[PDB]
């Protein structure tokens, strides 16, 4: 298992513009297009991301291309982030993937808002991190996904995904 397979499971793959769990226009593998309520604005952002007149539909390859870019950006974002970098550096490989998943999903800002958990993560207090992270909108809104991510961070294994 790896970060790509991990996210692919959590996000799925859709070749047509769709609304995410929060109601935002998305496509491919969890690629947020826009927060605006306009399908057109959505269609606009899409063509611009893809480089062609898509008409709200993309191919598998195009989806995977956005995906690659998105994972890369998530990783780079973490590493440039003052609050995230040190956590990341302190973790093992599996747990790192968990942090990338979170950032992919909620943004650097969003993850950066889990201060207390991040600090505990650095201290390697696994059970406490999981408890704390469960106390969040994130967990209440997408519980199954959140549980998978939390288990990963807690245990350091891919069990939640096998
Ligand atoms: Cl883009
Ligand atoms: Cl869920």
Image (cartoon, rainbow, N blue to C red):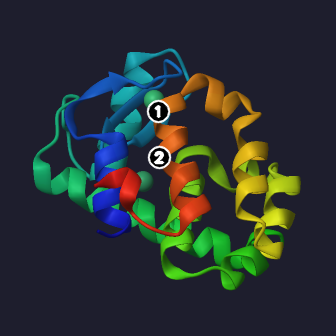
Side of 69 relative to 103 (left or right): left
Q: How many residues crowd mark 2 within 10 Å: few (<14), some (14–19), many (20+)?
A: some
Marker disc for residue 20? none
Q: Quadrant of the C terminus?
A: bottom left
Which quadrant of the structure image shows residue 20?
Answer: top left
Image: 110 above or below 93: above
Label 2 and label 1: CA atoms lie apart by 6 Å
**Mark 2, secondary structure of its residue:** helix
Q: Residue at x 45, y 39 (%)?
A: 32
**Mark 1, secondary structure of its residue:** helix
Q: Position of residue 17 (x, y in %)?
A: 28, 27
Front residue of 141/15: it is 141
Front residue of 49/11: it is 11
Q: Position of residue 41 (x, y in %)?
A: 44, 25
Image: 115 above or below 20: below
Q: Tell me if I can see residue 68 in this picture.
A: no
Side of 37 relative to 85 (left or right): left
Q: Residue at x 83, y 69 (%)?
A: 83
Marker disc for residue 144? 1
Side of 41 relative to 66 (left or right): right
Marks 2 and 1 in Cβ contact (< 8 Å): yes
Give the residue pinned by disc 2. Answer: 148
Q: Residue at x 32, y 24 (%)?
A: 18
Q: Position of residue 109 (x, y in %)?
A: 75, 51
Q: Residue at x 56, y 70 (%)?
A: 95
Badge 1 residue CB within 8 Å of ligand 2: yes
Which quadrant of the structure image shows residue 127?
Answer: bottom right
Q: How many residues crowd mark 1 within 10 Å: few (<14), some (14–19), many (20+)?
A: few
Image: 93 above or below 60: below
Q: Position of residue 49 (x, y in %)?
A: 36, 50
Image: 37 above or below 25: above
Q: Tell me if I can see residue 49 in this picture.
A: yes
């Amino acid at each position: 298992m790896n970060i790509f397979e991990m996210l692919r499971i959590d996000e799925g793959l859709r070749l047509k513009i769709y609304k995410d769990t929060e109601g935002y226009y998305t496509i491919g593998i969890g690629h947020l297009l826009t927060k605006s309520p306009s399908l057109n604005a959505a269609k606009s952002e899409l063509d611009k991301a893809i480089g062609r007149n898509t008409n709200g539909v993309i191919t598998k390859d195009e989806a995977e291309k956005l995906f690659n870019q998105d994972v890369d950006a998530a990783v780079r974002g973490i590493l440039r982030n003052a609050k995230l970098k040190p956590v990341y550096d302190s973790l093992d490989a599996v747990r790192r993937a968990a942090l990338i998943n979170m950032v992919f999903q909620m943004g650097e800002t969003g993850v950066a808002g889990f201060t207390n958990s991040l600090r505990m993560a650095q201290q390697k207090r696994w059970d406490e991190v999981a408890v704390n992270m469960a106390k969040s909108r994130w967990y209440n809104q997408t519980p199954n996904r959140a549980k998978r991510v939390i288990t990963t961070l807690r245990t350091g294994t891919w069990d939640a995904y096998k």
